[PDB]
Figure (cartoon, rainbow, N blue to C red):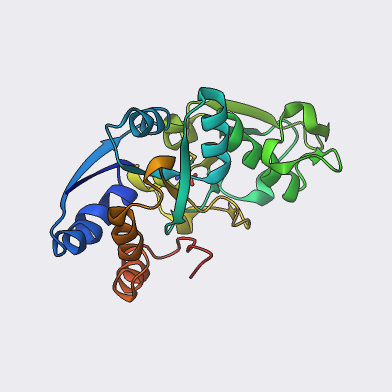
Amino acid sequence: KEIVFGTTVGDFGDMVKEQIQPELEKKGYTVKLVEFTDYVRPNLALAEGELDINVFQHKPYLDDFKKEHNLDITEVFQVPTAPLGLYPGKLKSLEEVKDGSTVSAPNDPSNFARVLVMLDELGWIKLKDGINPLTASKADIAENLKNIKIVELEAAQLPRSRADVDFAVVNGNYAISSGMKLTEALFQEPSFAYVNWSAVKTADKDSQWLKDVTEAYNSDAFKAYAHKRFEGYKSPAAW
Ligand code: MET
């Protein structure tokens, strides 16, 4: 049986090629990997049938996308994830913020919400009490304490937005594939609500191949591999 994986390019793809694929092949499976540079296509390819499983998103994004596009897909298990971080842009230290400082952020809703929550924790802005952090939007800002100019861009353009803004909040997969290091972040999201999940069409939730893939991502072997290959990543809660 052939298992077709869809992942964003870089780390999640490497997990498959370097570790998961060889493990599944020892069980007779032929594995195919399709890598994407964007966040939009994977879930569509999954629902269409082109992919049997994808690994590139967190639950809030999945939930948002599924609803918006009415797709019968669901999460299965979590994977080691590169954490979200606020990195040095033109300014190199949090201490250097000032009135009007610019901060770049991804512009899709589920990820943008994360930037606002991070700015609230830094005390740069103040979010209204009782709002859903998962859906925080500009309308949820009670006071822009430091008059921060939040610059929004397509998620993939964040690493290089650093040349044009004081600070840049970059998604981990893009930070890593752009030559950035997690240790370079000035502040990292403390939350664990965004550790990424693999997704599949609901129809395959109980399949045998998915059971094999699932244990391949949770064996001691994988855990050892992950510990040395992806230092600094947030681990699946189940671990
Ligand atoms: C498509 S949702 C964003 C996924 C990305 N790997 C992150 O954890 O920030």
